[PDB]
Length: 159
Length: 114
Image (cartoon, rainbow over all chains, first blue to last red; front, side, top):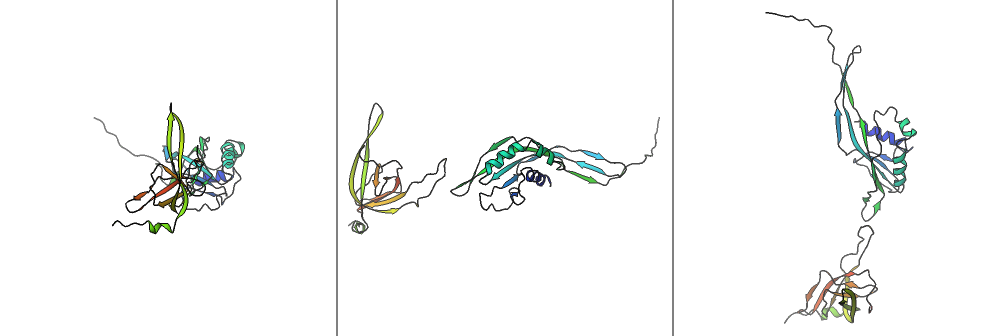
């Protein structure tokens, strides 16, 4: 839903990096000018749930179905400055700047797990491409207008 | 009367050296004498020489020669600056008066005499 876009936001203004140069994932988008170092938030990793909360509110009476989950979103950096935008990210991920800018992004951020300089077969040529891994954990939610119970009439019986 | 493409091969000729290796070994140590002869031939490109991908890129030119003289596999053919191992897609119309082979440039330097 919004999680991948959120982690894209976080990487947008942790690296102080451009809008148009962060594309999402295995969507359709042309990577022209290989040296223009792109970053893509690959979300192809299976997101697995952890719990299904259910809270209820009394006065402004509605309730709240939540679902905590996590996904191994990878980051692929491209371009001549792929390596740097890998390392400089893979290392600022756990600074002030990151941990201070991901304020409202309803999305935890775990440590970078591993890296790889797996390039891409660009047709008789090799374009710089680096993957960095980190589990991301978030929790989508929805709100539903149910209604409470004010009393309960009932009857008993005995032998 | 077997047809003989030989006369249909002279016009396109070119001088070229045909060598063969007869490996010699004692106590399993490799030495290689050479046998080189100036032979007639004709050369065209065989597989359009591409650039393969590996840890390091490499490329081997392909030529495919015809000649009236017999050409076994374990022989090299030098025409410009690098001998070609006579490895692939070869065929012997020997009874028809010629034979043909593809060629693989041995990126090793050319076997002069060793």
